[PDB]
Each structure stands twice: as C-alpha cells, then as structure tokens.
Image 1 (cartoon, rainbow, N blue to C red):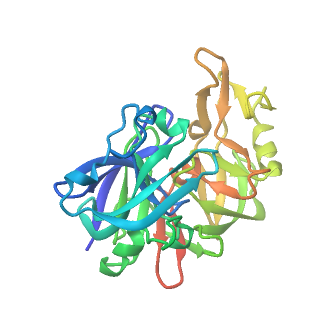
Image 2 (tube, rainbow, N blue to C red):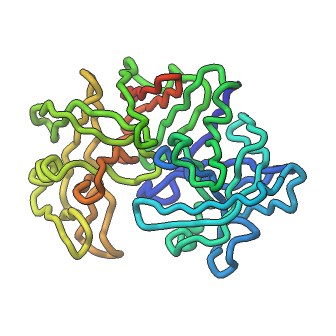
Image 3 (cartoon, rainbow, N blue to C red):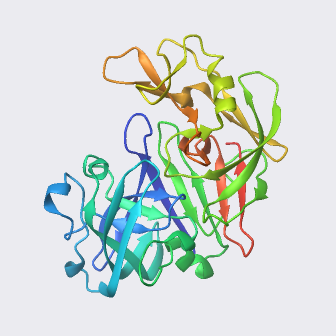
Length: 330
C-alpha cells in the first residue's frame, strides 16, 4: 500500500505545516502537525478541558463506531519548545492520504498547554520519530508509520515541505518526479529515538565549504534550523546589523537586509537553503527588526534540522531494518 497527503503551511511564515488525517468511523478529519521529532499521535478531543479549546477541530470518540478505549492507558508529553499535553487513549482507524491503519493509538487530550490552545490551526500532532519515544503508559504504543510499515510497498516515508507553499508527505514510495539529481543517503542513529544523522559541514552564501561533522536530528515539527553557536555566528556575521538579542531570544537582523544562503552537507552532496527561507519576519507587528531562521542550539543539547533546512530538500525517512535518511535537491 501507499499514501500521499498534501501538507500546508499554517501561516505566511511557514511556522508549521498541517496535514489532514481521517480518524474513526465515519471519518473525522483533523489537521495534524506531522512531527518526525516525536512519537505520539494526539488530538484535541471532546475530552479536552473546554477553556483550552479555541477553534480547533476535535475528535469525538463516542461518535466513532470503531473507537475503543485503551483501558488504563494515559499519556503526557513535553516538547522542546516548552509546550505540553496529556490525556487518555483510544484505538481507532486512522488514514493518511489513502493509507489506512486499524487499531492505531489515538491519544485524546484532556489538557493542553497555552501555546496549543492559542494555535487554532493545529488539531494535534502525528509523531513520526521512533516508537521508543512514545509516552503512553503503562503499555507504550506504536507510531502510525510503525503500524503501517509492513503493509507499505517500501518501508519509507518522504517529506517534501514547501516554502510559502503546500508540499507533500508520501508513505510507501519515493516519487522520482519530486526532486532533481540523486538522493544521497546517510546513516541514522536511533539511540535517542530520533532520526539522528551527521551533516558533513556547511557554507555561508558563496563562501567556501567548511568540512565539519554536525550531529543533529531531522525534525519536521521544529520550525527553525538550530546549529552550534560557532556555525550560527559565522552565518549572521555576513548580515550587516545582525545581532543576538537575549531579550528577543535569538538572532535578529534588519528587515531591510538581503540574507545569504546557507548550505549543509549530506555526505559529498550539498543542500542549499536560499536566504529568503531564513527570514521569519518582524519580531513584533510593525517592527523593522526581523527574526532569524538559523539559531543557536547551545543549551538545547542537540542540533535540529527543522523546517528551514528540510523544506530546501526532498527528504526520505527510510525505515528499513537499519534506518537511513536521504536528501535530494528539488
């Protein structure tokens, strides 16, 4: 089997992407944030504290003839950005782009943190990291991909995120029309539960490539590109007036600037992030200070190849017995 679904930016900055997902019978369609950095499929629901729902579409398990309470199971997750959610668990039928999993764990939120409430466009998350990170207790549950994998034509999914435009998540096949040149594959460590890999280096603008190993995670659920402070400083040094602002919480730059590109290595291959992808707009409405899309990972404890990086590529998440990651230009 295969599936193919369009993923759409939630706003004009590509702060996140939402993908429609069918849950239950009859289908209830929710727009979920597909997150290769976590492993829970959780939704706003009829059980979510009412004051914490503000415009989201909810899953109502009592209206699904295939929903079953997973007795005694609870979940609770905290994300790298400080947000969190928790609740109980149903199993139900979940379909993405024509690909159907029966008995998928659907984690129903009883509580969500303010940042989730405040984002009316995201109805929940669909985790695509390794199932070892799934938070369901006392019986850990599998991700949608893990459940689908054996049925797929090939045990892969691909992320093709757009810049200021829709893109695609495919399951079970590689669309050879969706990228240019070749896909370069690179080793993955699953030791921390992530799609963790090592970039071979970077360049700033038309500058020379610096060969250096950068371990990090391919994370569709993180907006920005978080890299070591040395790398980030080298980038922003090429933008007149750019500075790190502790008050704002990262590098900012004059909105009048033209940003240089940023290149990262995948083996001997190179992915070029155009400068415009690194512009996240005014820090507050009407400001001429703009927020940068490349930020330091210092104090995160891990480098993160988030959407800023991934949307410059066609990315293969290869879930073979030994997983790997593939990157192509597009």
